[PDB]
Amino acid sequence: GMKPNQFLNSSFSIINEQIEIYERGVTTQKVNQIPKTDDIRIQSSDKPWHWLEIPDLICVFVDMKGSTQLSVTRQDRTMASAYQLFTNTAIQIFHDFDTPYIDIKGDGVFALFNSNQIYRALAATVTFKTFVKEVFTPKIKQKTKGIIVGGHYGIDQKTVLVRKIGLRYNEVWAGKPINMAAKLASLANIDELLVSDRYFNNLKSDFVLKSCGCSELWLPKNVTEENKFDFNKAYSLTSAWCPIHGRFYCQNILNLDNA
Amino acid sequence: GMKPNQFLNSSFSIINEQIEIYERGVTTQKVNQIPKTDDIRIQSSDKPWHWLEIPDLICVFVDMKGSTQLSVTRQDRTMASAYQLFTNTAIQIFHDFDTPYIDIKGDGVFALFNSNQIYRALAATVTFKTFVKEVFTPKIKQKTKGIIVGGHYGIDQKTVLVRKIGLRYNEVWAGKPINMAAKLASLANIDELLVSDRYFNNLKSDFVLKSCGCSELWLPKNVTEENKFDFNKAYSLTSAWCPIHGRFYCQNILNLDNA
Ligand SMILES: [Cl-]
Ligand SMILES: [Cl-]
Ligand SMILES: [Zn+2]
Ligand SMILES: [Zn+2]
Image (cartoon, rainbow over all chains, first blue to last red; front, side, top):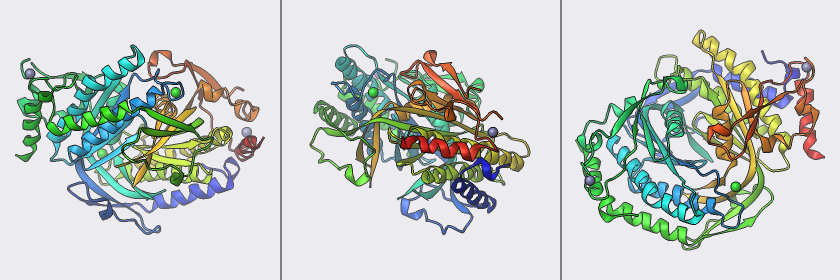
């Protein structure tokens, strides 16, 4: 129902071009793991959009929480320092866990994992969560003389589509889990990880379901009235790596993907 | 703080490296407009992080709303087509409005504008909003035989910091307006734009404050109890370009930045 006098001429022409592209339909092809970036082809502009379908991809999203009083303009520039200590550490930790794909969005970082990296994704997320709780929050509190800033985290797992868009070219991701992992992180309290029920249902080991004894780690949370999610239930983890047993637990959990 | 038995050895070493970087402090320098990407220098890794301070930068964030039933796996693959029709049109429209910087995050797109592009940012946002209402929503409803999918939108304006991080290199943005524009969009209803009070307070012309008569366009909304924003009030726009007067209004609004 678009009319010429409703839009700029250029906008009108662009919208009609996008309508034509949309009317071409799509094609897809299955690829079991996140492909190398150069294996994602740039298409000729006349073709129907082609997507690669990655099954049961895991998306972790971590975001700074409680930072509204941190500043980029006042003398201490504390938001700049906090951004580095939070985001750069997130990136380096996810890289150390051999994350297939990392990207930065606002005050947050998302990390994509393959469907056979369930436990690796969790171990990387809990490592970052523990860093934030034990290091980031105390140091920012020291610098600000009292402000408590931390993180909150979400994980979802679902099939996604990927292709490249030129703005160079970047991967673009269509589907549920990146959007849903970010929405879960936004819903989470400070120092809380929320995961979807479909991701939680893939966690089977007592190394991740029960504490070290220093109890059930995960609590269900109904998310239906949020009107944001295509699943009924999330699961909440508020604990972190044990100061005594955390390394041993992380070692075992990482190995759980190899079986 | 950190204990060695709480983390993997590699994670421990990485955290200590990030603490050292954080303890170097930061330096900043003012640049009045969003710089060219090659003017944002890559630093040697030993230096305190340097940031460019861009005053009163405008961030628009547009996001798909109501898409939980769209699928990337069922036969119609409707989420793939919808992603193209929504996101690619957003990209092309923002490029047509000469947006200095565009980036894609999940089901959404953000566009950054200079402080002297107040009205251009609004005109680009309302153009995309009108496209979504008049074109995207009807076509997706037709394809799905009834599902109503649309968009929601946020705008904030505040000083930001920018530098480059290598994961070639990408700009990273620290500060309020990208995070806050995304949170405003998440808070917005379908076919609703929410803007911060500080952005709204820069809107002075009746071309943006009053309708063509086919009334006040903006309604205040208190956002204090959201505990997410560093401002008290947002402003809601639910209208779109008039089917008769929309081109004329958009043209005049664009001209408002040149005075
Ligand atoms: Cl600030
Ligand atoms: Cl889906
Ligand atoms: Zn223990
Ligand atoms: Zn009118």
